[PDB]
Image (cartoon, rainbow, N blue to C red; front, top):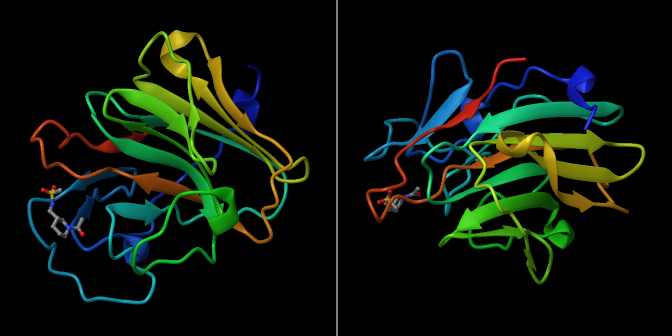
Amino acid sequence: HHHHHHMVHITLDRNTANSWLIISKDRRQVRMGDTHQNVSDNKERFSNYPMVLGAQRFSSGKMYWEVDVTQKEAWDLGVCRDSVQRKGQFSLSPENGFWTIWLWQDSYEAGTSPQTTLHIQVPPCQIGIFVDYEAGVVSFYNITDHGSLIYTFSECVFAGPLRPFFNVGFNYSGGNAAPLKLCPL
Ligand SMILES: CC(=O)N1CCC[C@H](CNS(C)(=O)=O)C1
């Protein structure tokens, strides 16, 4: 692909983070902590899942960023509406304001309803995410496999400002402690 020129500098918003997450000082990395991270509760925090939003809000234009997923067993990545539900149980779907892909139990899937099987021959260590607000497009690219397309959501109905969306996943296995990292431009 040739979307690299729409690269944007994404930072994580501490105030949206589940209370067990540890966001690095530069706001470019996030990982699961082994306990509550000693923060007060607020209405922005994701309560049920290890999720956090980017600080940036997008309402127009073309945007591109890259995320490092090296050695993780489980994660969700993409964009979501600024107004997504924060508390309680919910599914990742366009109907709920999310445009995401994920890794879970050795399979990759797109967050449609119901979910769609992805066909990845080269397990990605970095994922590229492209958003075209006007076109209603969210695309995912396998940076490890020369930028090969993973999935395109088209005819998206964003219906509001978008924020970068992250889930570091649970670490019940002891094999999913590694961080999500926003890769340099
Ligand atoms: C992320 C979160 O809200 N919580 C609360 C309940 C217990 C969970 C245990 N953490 S785990 C999967 O072992 O890494 C962590």
